[PDB]
Image: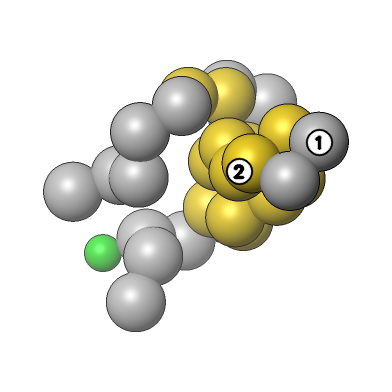
């Protein structure tokens, strides 16, 4: 389960993680 706000999204055939609360993005999955 990702923490609140976090969505796994598409980078072309890759993924990244976006947080809808803070608009932060990061490449690695949140811990
Ligand atoms: Cl959590």
Q: Is residue 10 visible?
A: yes
Q: Is residue 4 left or right of residue 16?
A: left
Q: Which residue is mark 1?
A: 12
- The secondary element bearing badge 1 is classed as loop
Is 2 rendered above or below residue 27? below
Q: Position of residue 12 (x, y in %)?
A: 81, 36
Q: Is residue 20 visible?
A: no
Q: Which residue is mark 2?
A: 15
| Colouring scheme applied when the structure was drawn | secondary structure
Residue positioned most to the bottom: 1
Whether the residues at callouts 1 and 2 have beta carbons within 8 Å, the answer is no
Residue ID at (18%, 48%): 31
Ligand 1 quadrant assignment = bottom left
Q: Position of residue 11 (x, y in %)?
A: 73, 34
On-image quarter of the N terminus: bottom left
Is 22 rendered above or below residue 21? above
Q: Position of residue 6 (x, y in %)?
A: 54, 53
- The secondary element bearing badge 2 is classed as strand
């Amino acid at each position: 389960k990702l923490p609140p706000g976090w969505e796994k999204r598409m980078s072309x055939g890759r993924v990244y993680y976006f947080n809808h609360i803070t608009n932060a993005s990061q490449w690695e999955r949140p811990s």
